[PDB]
């Protein structure tokens, strides 16, 4: 029981895992066992989704979050997102599930049987948190791994069947990406885009060529950065800027994950390219835009001239201008005029929505998709009654978009806290006052009084 | 040393009457800009077309408001989430019409209050303190982010962010209940538990310590004179307090460890208010309170109402009246 | 000690797991009956005959929706005793008429008296100043104003809060729509006391925990405290400097700080009670007359205060027919206030 | 104070002998209270078929104070 | 009150013939109506066209009359506008446009009868609340 | 007169803030 | 150690109805309209 109590380790049970900070072998165990839980969930959750799955109902009516992820990679789906074959869904779940037993094995072994520390046994695998060179080297290894991970996406997209392309001319379909975007002016341009409306920073990426080119860039950058970090030690300005400790490296990672969680929340909420509405359901903006399109269609069928119909406020009931003049849908959805979607773009001309096209060119499939998206807006209750908050029970629906946004906002938020907690604790422990104020060297007692 | 090293020494000085610090260097100007804009707008701004339907709502005192009805009104629904700084407008006249002051206030305020939180970490480091006061502050700060930024983002518009005024805040609450049934949301319920509990334990702790002050003063002088700033001895008897409280309820329902007791005082309202913030930030994406509308059915299929259904009837009243000229189509989807 | 009284006193004050005292003869049966009345009603009892509502687990309700509901408006402010002229000793009828409501309200009222006596009694025996009892007057003023005064000013107990989670929410929304209770400055002081109390709680607990002295070796710092130790476990000096430099002002006197922690939320709840006494009489803070005159004469004048009254009028029209069934409200569709489309 | 610690009591074989019988007997007694329908008649709660008569369009609301008991009785007779 | 054989007896055709549904068909009808229809017709209304509801009286004045099993079954095969002038299979789910309304692909004739049965029975239970919308919640 | 009164009370509070901070009773460690 | 104490009565005035009620509510989960 080598330091598995509070007396020996100085950490209570509820801070139990802090006991692992300088026990590299047991800590590797914690980490491998953990990845096992992650890979486990992925495989079992996939299988559960597949067992519950009725191919003829939209994914988004079935509470699915993982199958949609698989389908977007182009597996199991065809034109319009029609499921042609569930076996890839099956393969993905099984292989994760089996793999998790292997990780679980490794994890349990290192946690409970192998050497508690790895430094005596091996210098390659051993490490000291304060060894700035080892730390950048491990980091460097994982950067190379991550880089290859990005290149696997590219490989799928260009050489192994392509990706689901909601924008595919003629309708959504799987499509091979042959000409990915390589121009750094485009790829790095996205990073300098404003995060506000009508801009959306990286969340705006609206074609697979950009998505593929971006991953080409990232795979290269990450492998390059990995090599760099294996070959180098930190410059002195970096040495002087950071806390160098297990708890501090955790805190930096916590900050970056919180940030990524937040980005992920906005991605799934707004983006319908890498989260195709065919699989994930319509975005909030999209559903709101679909309602105005639905009634524009209905009312014009009834004889309404939609261009000159003045609403109660004096703005056009169906159509109006954005603050920069573009023709856009009216009523509340004015806010959503930045929305772009494949069922809608055919009506858009250079000035925004085109009245000639609206009067003549609205196809039945557009009416159909707008009705569908209007009635699958991402609104529902925690007990999964779909609808507005005043809706009666009947429809069992919460959009996959709401589940993915809400969960990840919560996760990103607590990770930010985790970051503040650990950053502040790491700072204090590095300076030596994390356990409290020395009663005989109280800093404030040595300072001039304020007034 | 050099001019820069002197500057750094001053910024980070533990001796300034108000700590400045690196977070302070961002906090001071942003908070001043927000404060100044807020005060001027609250007194003098013209009416703002909050819902982008050319229906300007008067927020300021000079345009017919009092302290209670007054507000800095959210920016126009026609703007949505577009960034609307002063230089994006053709004139200040236009800027004021469209609610530009609101974006200026809430953006400088959020940056400033985030730095206010960083500054709290910073000073505690300069003073050799443990670092988590800033974490307690993350709870109100998260709540402010929920109503001024996250909610607008989810709903596609700053016109749905909380208005910067008293009656405005109530408007936001009421529309929120209609659209999300926030009362039936368990994160809001944890929030209530958090603030009701926070009040309770405050009244409790205050009262337990006070009841236990050691006799140090005359029958005429304030008991506060019994405690001197900086004294080393503890001014009340915690064993007597525990003797009382442990008997009020039962022994183990009571704290004799001041440290775990003060921990519980920090944790209870902070965690509950985190859930409140997260309630608002997750209803931002339309995951709403429990819906038990028509949940009880009789043998024939007659709906038997519950108190959930009477809640529904009140929510419906709010729904159909709110923004009475803004909807043209039958469903309110944001 | 002498006579039977003193012997009984001995027994009542024995140092046991659950103190009893004289206050216990009041406290314990009334707290237990109020609570078991609540659990019994929410588990098995309907509200069909009083409200047209299901309200128990037996009928299909869940934890958020069960309640012990108020009696029917036709009952007035009847005590509704089991043996009263309404139920006439019939237990089933009593349950059906709302008898559990007054049962829980009155036993709860006497239980609360008992608890506060228990606070005076324990403090007297331990030899402390009875500040805790005094602080508890705030919960008392709230219970009495809201559960007793309010419905006593209104037409009947029907309009008191019903004992249930969703029922209490309904109570909230009724107060907004009918009384515009958010506008009321006594409710606003209540909010300040409750949110200020919660702030004071968070901020004091966090300040102590972050200016602790190192009195141990453990990285978990809870063990480095001794109940009988002479010294402060944290530095008031550092805490004071920290807040002075952060916020501009700080406490310097620990007795003040704690007294203030009693004062703020207690005073808050007392203020809300006064407003609720006002609402017993429909003496609302409903309107600002100057806004109404301007708005009546100027159809382009709009404020958040006008916007919220349109919400209230929506709430009244839409909830009243099912919420006040004894009024037999029939509001044909054409009369209902509604904005465009919705 | 005095009483035996809970820790002692609930780890003692004698505790489990007594309560392996009393806990389930109470639970089952609770269950029967509902399954026999006994709960409905003690408390006067309607079963799913007893809220409304077959063609009734309105709620049996009590509207009389001193003969409300008799009204419920009347309301109960026509079901 | 109970879900009795009388409540479950509904017009089969335009000529006055009735059919008594079993409790099982009713439940089936409610289930399948949720599965395929309630996203637009929750409560007897129509989200995407509120002028048209599923009230019996409304159905009776459609062309052809839809206030009976046969009429509803035929609607579900080959839906028309309310005056019967136009075939709207391309934008309203039916057996005819099961290619584009995929939830229609495994509805059997018996399923269609069950849904028709649900639509005719609900207003007999719910009255004006069926097709009433939020006023009646 | 009404706006003036509101702004005047407000301004008195802001001034009261400045004195409470900068011209407080100094805390004395004795 | 005694067995029948105040603590003992207090515990059972609560624990006894509680289990009885839990069985009652468990049975309710199987009621259908
Ligand atoms: C190191 C850290 C230091 C930080 C320093 C501060 C730097 C400034 C940060 C800016 C803050 C962002 C505010 C605006 C956020 C927003 O409106 O975000 C939205 C954008 C998405 O923008 C949307 O992007 C969309 C992209 O979709 C478009 O393109 C799509 C392609 O398929 C579709 O076609 C879609 O229909 C189409 O409209 C559109 O442009 C929308 O108009 C546009 O609104 O998300 C994004 O940019 C992603 C990034 C935003 C992060 C989320 C904010 C959370 C903040 C933390 C809160 C917690 C704090 C707690 C404290 C305790
Ligand atoms: C992802 C969750 C996770 C993981 C991976 C770990 C991992 C670890 N913990 Mg932490 N811990 C956790 C969560 C976790 N913990 C939580 C939630 C708490 C609060 C309750 C703690 C509180 C805590 C304390 C107080 C301590 C640890 C310690 C440890 C380490 C030693 C364990 C030991 O000695 O057990 C001995 C236990 C057993 C022999 C029982 C069996 C345990 C095995 C691993 C169960 C495996 C079952 C699994 C289904 C097998 C699959 C097999 C198949 C693949 C073939 C180990 C690396 C200890 C420490 O740090 O040591 C230096 C320590 O003192 N933990
Ligand atoms: C990224 C996380 C994530 C997301 C977005 C989803 C989303 C979804 N799931 Mg998957 N799932 C997850 C993780 C997730 N789940 C995990 C970890 C498990 C294993 C337990 C599952 C196992 C699972 C099953 C078995 C099922 C789903 C189903 C569903 C759907 C309905 C969910 C529901 O009704 O919740 C109801 C809501 C809750 C239970 C409330 C969650 C509240 C948490 C506990 C609050 C705590 C917050 C924070 C984490 C705590 C911090 C504390 C603080 C003090 C520090 C929805 C599409 C259902 C389905 O439709 O499948 C097709 C279904 O049957 N899930
Ligand atoms: C990244 C996690 C990780 C790391 C850093 C280590 C590191 C270590 N392990 Mg542990 N272990 C892991 C995970 C890990 N292991 C897993 C998943 C299992 C179950 C299979 C084990 C089971 C295990 C046992 C039973 C033992 C070790 C031992 C060792 C030591 C020597 C290993 C060696 O020299 O091989 C050199 C390299 C090779 C032999 C070739 C490796 C071939 C790999 C598997 C293929 C390439 C993998 C590729 C990158 C894809 C990975 C999958 C990924 C996508 C998830 C060293 C401390 C030994 C020990 O600690 O000594 C006392 C020992 O007995 N490991
Ligand atoms: C997980 C990924 C990761 C991590 C944790 C690190 C960590 C580290 N890197 Mg390495 N690096 C990586 C990936 C990574 N690197 C990759 C992929 C490359 C190839 C491009 C590099 C190439 C590289 C170089 C060339 C150098 C490092 C250096 C360092 C060290 C200090 C870095 C620092 O202070 O930045 C913090 C950032 C700054 C100091 C810049 C100023 C801050 C700006 C204003 C922030 C703006 C961002 C803002 C939030 C907005 C985000 C979006 C934006 C794009 C608009 C540290 C060991 C240094 C070193 O010590 O090398 C040995 C160094 O010189 N790295
Ligand atoms: C401290 C204990 C306590 C207190 C203060 C109360 C108080 C109350 N109970 Mg509760 N109750 C208790 C314990 C208590 N109960 C216990 C242990 C049980 C289980 C048996 C009950 C079961 C119960 C039921 C079933 C009901 C109440 C009700 C009531 C209310 C009316 C009582 C009344 O009118 O009495 C009148 C009697 C007295 C006040 C006693 C007078 C004592 C004086 C000092 C002496 C006079 C004696 C007299 C002269 C001699 C006989 C007269 C003869 C000459 C004709 C009131 C809130 C009713 C209620 O809640 O309705 C909504 C109701 O229906 N109780
Ligand atoms: C929360 C309520 C509460 C509390 C905590 C106290 C506390 C105190 N009272 Mg005050 N008191 C109260 C309410 C309260 N009082 C009320 C409502 C009155 C009536 C006006 C009084 C009248 C009073 C006097 C005249 C005196 C005190 C005094 C005292 C002190 C000693 C204890 C005592 O005498 O209790 C008295 C006991 C109680 C308040 C509990 C009474 C329990 C009753 C009898 C139960 C009745 C059951 C009922 C008949 C059921 C029928 C219900 C019906 C609706 C159907 C202490 C400061 C004495 C003092 O100040 O010493 C210096 C003192 O002289 N009390
Ligand atoms: C360390 C530690 C811990 C943790 C641990 C862990 C975390 C572990 C993990 C583990 C794991 C992670 C495990 C896993 C496993 C797995 C498995 C075992 C699997 C298998 C599979 C199978 C067998 C399959 C089958 C199938 C198929 C093939 C097909 C389909 C169907 C089915 C599914 C049937 C704790 C906290 C306790 C504490 C103490 C210490
Ligand atoms: C994939 C993709 C793409 C691309 C992408 C990219 C290209 C990215 C990049 C990215 C990047 C490139 C990023 C960066 C980041 C960074 C950061 C995040 C930073 C941070 C920093 C820090 C944190 C610092 C800190 C500090 C300070 C500030 C001061 C002093 C101290 C210290 C050092 C602490 C696109 C969109 C095209 C399309 C889609 C897909
Ligand atoms: C009224 C009345 C009376 C009385 C009665 C009584 C006294 C009763 C009691 C009763 C009772 C005394 C009952 C109990 C119950 C209980 C229950 C029913 C429970 C439940 C619980 C649960 C369900 C749990 C939950 C939870 C929580 C709370 C948190 C943690 C987690 C969980 C979720 C587990 C007399 C005869 C005098 C006369 C006439 C009237
Ligand atoms: C560990 C990763 C092993 C992945 C196995 C490669 C499957 S690659 C394979 O390639 C085809 C086109 O060539 C696609 O049409 C097909 O969907 C895809 O699965
Ligand atoms: C029922 C509670 C009322 C208690 C107050 C009345 C006390 S009365 C008191 O009691 C003595 C014994 O202690 C007797 O010896 C004595 O004769 C009698 O006057
Ligand atoms: O803006 Mn403010 O309030 Ca959110 O919901 Mn839609 O939009 Mn408007 O109505 Mn309801
Ligand atoms: Cl409004
Ligand atoms: Cl609209
Ligand atoms: Fe304290």
Image: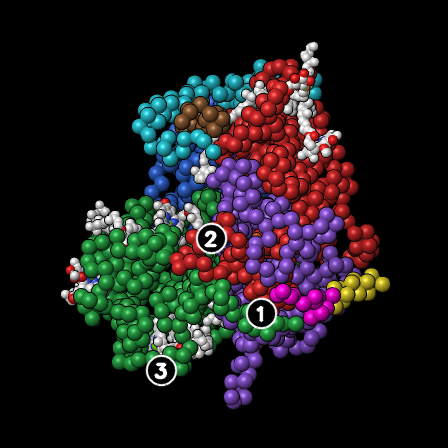
Chain colours: A green, B purple, C red, D cyan, E blue, F yellow, G brown
Q: Position of residue A82 (x, y in %)?
A: 33, 55
Q: Position of residue A420 (x, y in %)?
A: 46, 64
Mark 2 sits near ligand 16, with its Cβ under 8 Å away: no
Query: Which residue bears the numbered disc 3?
Result: A235
Side of C157 where B12 appears, left or right: left
> Alpha carbon of mark 3 to alpha carbon of mark 1: how far?
32 Å
Query: Which residue bears the numbered disc 2?
Result: C225
Q: How dense is the environment of label 1, judged by Cα within 10 Å: few (below 14), some, or many (20 and up)?
A: many
Disc 3 + disc 1, Cβ < 8 Å:
no
Q: Nearer the viewer, residue A148 or E30?
A: A148
Task: Identify the image quadrant of residue A416.
Answer: bottom left
- Please identify, in this view, whether the residue under mark 3 or under mark 1 is nearer the observer: 3
Note whether residue B222 is visible: yes
Q: Position of residue A206 (x, y in %)?
A: 42, 69
- Is F27 covered by the magenta stretch? yes
User: Looking at the image, which residue sits at the far front?
Assistant: C1
- The secondary element bearing badge 3 is classed as loop
- Is A417 covered by the magenta stretch? no
Q: Position of residue C167 (x, y in %)?
A: 59, 36
> Alpha carbon of mark 2 to alpha carbon of mark 3: how far?
44 Å
Note whether residue B148 is visible: no
> Alpha carbon of mark 2 to alpha carbon of mark 1: how far?
37 Å
Chain letter, disc 2 residue: C
- The secondary element bearing badge 1 is classed as helix
Mark 3 sits near ligand 5, with its Cβ under 8 Å away: yes
User: At 78% from the left edge and 57% from the top edge, which residue is drawn?
Assistant: C299
Which region shows up in magenta?
A: F16-30
């Amino acid at each position: 029981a080598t330091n598995r109590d509070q007396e020996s380790s100085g950490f209570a049970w509820w801070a139990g895992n802090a006991r692992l900070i300088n026990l590299s072998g047991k800590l590797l165990g914690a980490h491998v066992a953990h990845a096992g839980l992650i890979v486990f969930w992925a495989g079992a959750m996939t299988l559960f989704e597949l067992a519950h799955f009725i191919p003829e109902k939209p994914m988004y009516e079935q509470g699915l979050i993982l199958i949609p992820h698989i389908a977007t990679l182009g597996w199991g789906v065809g034109p319009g997102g029609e499921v042609v074959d569930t076996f890839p869904f099956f393969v993905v779940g099984v292989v994760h599930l089996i793999s998790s037993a292997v990780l679980g094995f490794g994890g349990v072994y290192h946690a409970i049987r192998g050497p508690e520390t790895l430094e005596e046994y091996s210098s390659f695998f051993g490490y000291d948190w304060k060894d700035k060179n080892k730390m950048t080297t491990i980091l460097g290894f994982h950067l190379i791994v991550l880089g290859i991970g990005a290149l696997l996406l590219v490989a799928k997209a260009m050489f192994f069947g392509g990706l689901y392309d909601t924008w595919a001319p003629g309708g959504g379909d799987v499509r091979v990406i042959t000409n990915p975007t390589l121009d750094p002016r485009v790829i790095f341009g996205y990073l300098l885009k404003s995060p506000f409306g009508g801009e959306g920073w990286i969340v705006s990426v609206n074609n697979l060529e950009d998505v593929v080119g971006g991953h080409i860039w990232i795979g290269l950058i990450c492998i390059a950065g990995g090599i760099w970090h294996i070959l180098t030690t930190p410059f002195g300005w970096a040495r002087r800027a950071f806390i160098w400790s297990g708890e501090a490296y955790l805190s930096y990672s916590l900050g970056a994950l919180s940030m990524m969680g937040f980005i992920a929340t906005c991605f799934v909420w707004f983006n319908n390219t890498v989260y195709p509405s065919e699989f994930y359901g319509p975005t909030g903006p999209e559903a709101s835009q679909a309602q105005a399109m639905t009634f524009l269609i209905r009312d014009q069928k009834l004889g309404a001239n939609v261009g000159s119909a003045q609403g109660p406020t004096g703005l056009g009931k169906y159509l109006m201008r954005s603050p920069t003049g573009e023709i856009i849908f009216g009523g509340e959805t004015m806010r959503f005029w930045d929305f772009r979607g494949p069922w809608l773009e055919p009506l858009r001309g250079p000035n925004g929505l085109d009245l000639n096209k609206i009067k003549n060119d609205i196809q039945p499939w557009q009416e159909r998709r707008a009705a569908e998206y209007m009635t699958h807006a991402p609104l529902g209750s925690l007990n999964s009654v779909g609808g507005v908050a005043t809706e009666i029970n009947s429809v069992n629906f919460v959009s996959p978009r709401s589940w993915l946004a809400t969960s990840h906002f919560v996760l990103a938020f607590f990770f930010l806290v985790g970051h503040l907690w650990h950053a502040g604790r790491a700072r204090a422990a590095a300076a030596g006052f994390e356990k409290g104020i020395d009663r005989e060297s109280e800093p404030v007692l040595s300072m001039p009084s304020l007034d | 040393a050099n001019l820069w090293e002197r500057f750094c020494n001053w910024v980070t000085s533990t001796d300034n009457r108000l700590y400045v610090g690196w977070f302070g260097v961002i906090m001071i100007p942003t908070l001043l800009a927000a404060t100044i804009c807020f005060v001027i707008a609250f007194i003098a701004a013209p009416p703002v077309d909050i819902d982008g339907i050319r229906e300007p709502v008067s927020g300021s005192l000079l345009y017919g408001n009092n302290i209670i009805t007054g507000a800095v009104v959210p920016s126009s629904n026609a703007i949505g989430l577009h960034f609307y700084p002063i230089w994006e407008a053709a004139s200040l006249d236009e800027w004021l019409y469209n609610g530009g002051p609101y974006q200026l206030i809430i953006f400088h305020f959020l940056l400033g209050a985030s730095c206010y939180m960083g500054r709290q970490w910073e000073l505690s480091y300069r003073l050799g303190m443990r670092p988590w006061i800033c974490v307690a502050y993350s709870a109100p700060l998260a709540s402010a982010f929920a109503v001024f930024l996250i909610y607008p983002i989810g709903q596609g518009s700053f016109s749905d962010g909380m208005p910067l005024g008293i009656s405005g805040t109530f408007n936001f609450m009421i529309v929120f209940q209609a659209e999300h049934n926030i009362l039936m949301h368990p994160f809001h319920q944890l929030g209530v538990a958090g603030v009701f509990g926070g009040a309770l334990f405050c009244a409790m702790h205050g009262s337990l310590v006070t009841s236990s002050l050691i006799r140090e003063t005359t029958e005429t002088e304030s008991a506060n004179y019994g405690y001197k700033f900086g004294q080393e001895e503890e001014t009340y008897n915690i064993v007597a307090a525990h003797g009382y409280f442990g008997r009020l309820i039962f022994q183990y329902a009571s704290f004799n460890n001041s440290r775990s007791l003060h921990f519980f005082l920090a944790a209870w309202p902070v965690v509950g208010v985190w859930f409140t913030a997260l309630g608002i930030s997750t209803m931002a994406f339309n995951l709403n309170g429990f819906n038990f509308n028509h949940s009880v059915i009789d043998a024939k299929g007659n709906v038997i109402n519950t108190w959930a259904d009477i809640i529904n009837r009140a929510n419906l009243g709010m729904e159909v009246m709110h923004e009475r000229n803004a909807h043209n189509f039958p469903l309110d989807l944001a | 000690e002498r006579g039977w009284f003193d012997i009984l006193d001995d027994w009542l004050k024995r140092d046991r797991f659950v103190f009893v005292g004289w206050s216990g003869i009041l406290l314990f049966p009334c707290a237990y009956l109020a609570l078991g009345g609540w659990l019994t009603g929410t588990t098995f009892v309907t509200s069909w005959y009083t409200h047209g509502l299901a309200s128990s687990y037996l009928e299909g309700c869940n934890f958020l929706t069960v309640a012990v509901s108020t009696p029917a408006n036709s009952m007035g402010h009847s005590l509704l005793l089991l043996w009263g002229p309404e139920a006439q000793g019939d237990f089933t009828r009593w349950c059906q008429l709302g008898g559990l409501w007054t049962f829980i309200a009155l036993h709860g009222a006497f239980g609360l008296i008992g608890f506060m006596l228990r606070q005076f009694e324990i403090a007297r025996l331990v030899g402390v100043r009875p500040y805790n009892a005094i602080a508890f007057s705030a919960p008392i003023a709230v219970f009495v104003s809201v559960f007793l005064i309010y419905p006593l000013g209104q037409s009947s107990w029907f309009f008191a809060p019903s004992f249930g989670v969703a029922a209490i929410f309904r109570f909230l929304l009724f107060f907004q729509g009918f009384h515009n209770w958010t506008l009321n400055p006594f409710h606003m002081m209540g909010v300040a006391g409750v949110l200020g109390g919660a702030l004071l709680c968070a901020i004091h607990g966090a300040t102590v925990e972050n200016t602790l002295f190192q009195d141990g070796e453990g990285a978990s710092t809870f063990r480095a405290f001794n109940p009988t130790q002479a010294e402060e476990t944290y530095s008031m000096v550092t805490a004071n400097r920290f807040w002075s430099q952060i916020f501009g002002i700080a406490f310097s006197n620990k007795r003040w700080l704690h007294f203030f922690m009693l004062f703020v939320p207690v005073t808050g709840l007392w203020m809300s009670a006064i407003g609720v006494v006002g609402l017993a009489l429909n003496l609302r803070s409903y309107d600002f007359i100057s806004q109404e005159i301007r708005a009546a004469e100027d159809p382009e004048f709009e404020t958040f205060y006008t916007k919220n009254l349109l919400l209230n009028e929506g709430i009244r029209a839409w909830m009243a027919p099912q919420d006040q069934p004894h009024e037999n409200f029939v509001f044909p569709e054409e009369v209902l206030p509604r904005g465009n489309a919705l | 104070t005095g009483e035996r610690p809970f820790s002692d009591i609930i780890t003692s074989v004698r505790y489990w002998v007594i309560h392996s019988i009393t806990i389930p007997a109470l639970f089952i007694a609770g269950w029967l209270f509902v399954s026999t329908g006994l709960a409905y008649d003690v408390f006067g709660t309607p079963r799913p078929d007893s809220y409304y008569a077959q063609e009734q369009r309105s709620i049996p609301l009590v509207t009389d104070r001193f003969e409300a008991k008799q009204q419920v009785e009347t309301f109960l007779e026509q079901l | 009150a109970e879900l009795t054989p009388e409540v479950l007896t509904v017009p089969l055709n335009s000529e006055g013939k009735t059919i008594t549904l079993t409790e099982k068909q009713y439940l089936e009808g409610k289930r399948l109506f949720q599965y395929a229809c309630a996203s637009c017709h929750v409560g007897g209304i129509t989200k995407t066209n509120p002028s048209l509801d599923l009230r019996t009286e409304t159905l009776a004045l459609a062309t052809p009359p839809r206030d009976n099993i046969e009429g509803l079954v035929d609607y579900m095969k080959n839906p028309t506008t309310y005056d019967g002038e136009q075939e709207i299979a391309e934008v309203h789910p039916s057996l005819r446009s099961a290619d584009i309304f995929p939830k229609m692909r495994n509805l059997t004739e018996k399923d269609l009868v069950a849904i028709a049965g649900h639509i005719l029975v609900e207003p007999k239970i719910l009255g004006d609340k069926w097709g009433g919308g939020k006023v009646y919640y | 007169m009404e706006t003036i009164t509101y702004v005047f009370i407000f301004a008195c509070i802001i001034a009261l803030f400045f004195f409470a901070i900068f011209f407080r009773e100094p805390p004395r460690i004795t | 150690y005694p067995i029948f104490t105040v603590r003992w009565v207090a515990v059972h005035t609560l624990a006894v109805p509680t289990i009885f009620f839990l069985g009652a509510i468990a049975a309710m989960q199987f009621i259908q309209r």
